[PDB]
Image (spheres, rainbow, N blue to C red):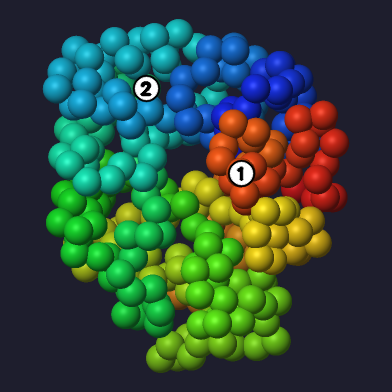
Amino acid sequence: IGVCYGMSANNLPAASTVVSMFKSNGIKSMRLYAPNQAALQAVGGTGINVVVGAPNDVLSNLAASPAAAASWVKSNIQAYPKVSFRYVCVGNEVAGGATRNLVPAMKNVHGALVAAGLGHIKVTTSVSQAILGVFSPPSAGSFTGEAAAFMGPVVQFLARTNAPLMANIYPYLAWAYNPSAMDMGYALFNASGTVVRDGAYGYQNLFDTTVDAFYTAMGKHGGSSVKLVVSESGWPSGGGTAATPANARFYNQHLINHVGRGTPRHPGAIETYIFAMFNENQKDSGVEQNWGLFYPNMQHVYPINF
């Protein structure tokens, strides 16, 4: 499975040590949110797959010039011939206005990559489950109107380039919003049976419901051929309602065991990245500083089998 290597902390291990943690725990993929040189130099030649992202503040730059895109690829992708790049995630949850630069930046990075003969590395973007206006039942999946306005061209692009869509999916967050609306077990991979019967499909967990809702919404804009990659998913071990190591372990371990099967309407392993490797101490107090599978001190927050 994959794990998101977030670095919004002032006390993490050296990149090299982190890379050993991936290796020994059997974490096959890594997600970076920006071309970190130390991490990229470390991960090279290890067989760990890497999703390298382009920060949201450089999009306008990648969108404006093809040559800009080219330079980026030369310094951030080409500079590292021994790393195993899977995708280049242009933007992470890009909100209003800036979304105007989404497709152009994506087109430019893509062309730069094809020009270098590295077209095996897919360009995509990562969206937030918050873009779903309706997510239940799955057949009634749909984007908000704000998202609907920019998601069309993005989805079609992906379809044209045979690239997936990446979605940051958190049942915990859907549930926490109004704990009175749904039962926590439904979100925790701990429901007894079907909670939602959609047509001839029955959902037993909020992860599937969302993923399938995404597919339905994507379909409405010519994305029926595009695959979804879960670029983030997790549950916090402290800082809020239901935030404990017992719950976070129950959630993460079931996620890990679950993804290879797929969903009711989409059977087949879903590429998944768990958020995140460590607790991040530079985030705002609350659950944000508790997504980590590990403490900076390198100890597991709870036991997990990857």
Helix, strand or loop at label 1? It is: loop
Query: Residue beneath label 2, please?
Result: 118
Most foreground residue, 143 or 256: 143
Residue 155 in view, yes or no: yes
Mark 2 is surrounded, within 10 Å at the Cα level, by few (under 14), some (14 to 19) or many (20 or more) other residues, namely some
Three-letter amino acid code of the residue under disc 1:
Ser
Whichever of callouts 2 and 1 sits on the residue coming sooner in the sequence is 2
Query: Residue beneath label 1, please?
Result: 285
Does residue 198 sit above or below 261 in this rendering?
A: below
Residue 182, image x, y percentages: 55, 81
Does residue 159 sit above or below 225 in this rendering?
A: above
Does residue 276 sit above or below 147 in this rendering?
A: above
Residue 187, image x, y percentages: 60, 72
Three-letter amino acid code of the residue under disc 2:
Leu
Residue at x 25%, y 33% (from the top left corner): 106
Which mark lies nearer to you, 2 or 1? 1
Q: Furthest residue to the front? A: 285
CA separation, marks 2 and 1?
41 Å
Please indicate whether residue 82 sits to the left or right of residue 294 in the image.
Answer: left
Please indicate whether residue 80 sits to the left or right of residue 119 in the image.
Answer: right
Residue at x 59%, y 88% (from the top left corner): 194
